[PDB]
Length: 158
Length: 157
Ligand SMILES: C[As](C)(=O)[O-]
Ligand SMILES: C[As](C)(=O)[O-]
Ligand SMILES: [Cl-]
Image 1 (cartoon, protein in one colour):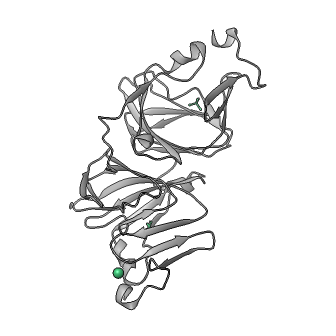
Image 2: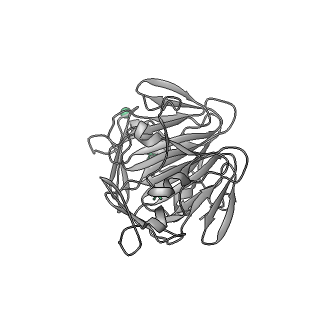
Image 3: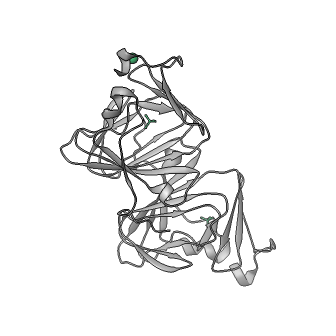
């Protein structure tokens, strides 16, 4: 049965961010549509942002292409060029390696949802625009460090 | 990074051979992934006029595929038969799973869907409803019977 049942898919909350940063994703939840569907080459997540919530800390990927479509509510795409409003049907593309850190923020008083597609790759590196952090992802998970590879500090993550 | 859908070229027609070419009358699409500079997967927004179909019923060997209906109502046709699909409904087709699929617009209203497909150097698609397959690569693509011999007059006119 290729047709997915969204009401059955587990709703995920929280984040992999370290220390105080985990709290930054309060109001973000998601359904992993790709995994539910048995796909392995890319991920597909339907992400829901409560009022005030954000999709991620502002970043860009080195290895994975990313595509987003807003499905409901209204969002703000924040990148190097500033704020870009996004309504339902609006789409954004983030080519792997393009050093323009991006995030979506819900500044409205209603929930907003968006579809995000990202290539699955054995390894990944993301750089965070707004602070001295980067992450290295492999099959075992995520290693967050400063941009020089040294550990994140208490001053940084509590 | 924000795409302008009114600016992207609307594509029509099909690469299907002979009489099958016209089978995709009423199908048009916007290549969103190319528009956006993406290389690792394709994203197409496909519009089906009433009666139109997404493709001849088929499955991919090498590429994963994902679909969400964005507007209107469609029918997903696969081995198990007909499955109605309304806006927000999604379907996933893992590479290699031999369950051929197509979308058909049996309403009187246009319907649109988003399709994502992995880009790979080579691909094979088998067609479920007739003796045909297609092999693709960098060099190009070729429609043949499933045994690799040429499609016949009896088959494609
Ligand atoms: C761990 As991330 C690339 O969603 O900030
Ligand atoms: C759109 As097709 C997989 O029948 O070439
Ligand atoms: Cl035949």
